Image (cartoon, rainbow, N blue to C red):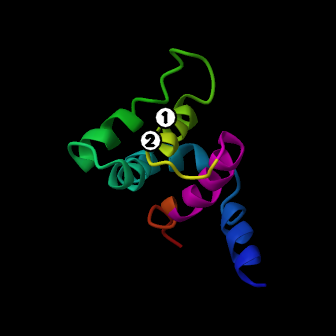
């Protein structure tokens, strides 16, 4: 298969260092993805709490735990193990827009 390659190619197209800026903008966009399945109040309203879920109030996985909580509400078959993995590739697209050349 090719999809396996292009996918991991995205994950390593701009090192890990870009991925730290990726999360910050992508947080909004991930909010929308989960908010759409849970059918909350507003898309941007759940997204605003994602760009605040990175605060180390509780410790680690602060953004990720938020995503999982919603995955139970939506009743999808995805564990915390897979969430972090999905986040990497999802972030690789989130930096494509930021990347000039």
Residue at x 50%, y 48% (from the top left corner) = 75
Q: Which residues are magenta?
A: 79-93
Q: Is residue 72 left or right of residue 79?
A: left
The foreground one among 55 and 75 is: 75
Residue 57 % position (x, y): 50, 15
The foreground one among 59 and 37 is: 37
The disc at residue 73 is 2
Which is closer to the viewer, label 1 or label 2?
2
The disc at residue 66 is 1
Residue 15 % position (x, y): 70, 56
1 or 2: tag closer to the N-terminus? 1
Residue 66 % position (x, y): 49, 34
User: Could you say whether the residue bearing mark 2 is in a helix, strand or loop?
Assistant: helix
Residue at x 72%, y 70% (from the top left corner) = 9
> What crowding class fits label 2: few (fewer than 14 Cα within 10 Å), some (14-19), or many (20 or more)?
few
Q: Is residue 81 above or below residue 33?
A: above
The N terminus: image quadrant: bottom right
Q: Is residue 85 left or right of residue 95?
A: right
Residue at x 73%, y 67% (from the top left corner) = 8
């Amino acid at each position: 298969m090719q999809d396996r390659e292009k996918a991991f190619e995205a994950k390593f197209a701009l090192d890990e260092e870009l991925r730290f800026k990726a999360t910050a903008r992508r947080n909004k966009l991930l909010g929308l993805w989960a908010a759409g399945l849970l059918a909350k109040s507003d898309p941007e309203a759940y997204a605003s709490e994602i760009v605040a879920a990175d605060f180390e109030e509780a410790g680690h996985e602060d953004v990720v735990r938020k995503i999982k909580t919603d995955f139970d509400a939506a009743g999808v078959a995805i564990s915390e193990d897979d969430i972090r993995v999905r986040m990497i590739e999802l972030l690789s697209e989130a930096v494509a827009q930021l990347q000039k050349n």
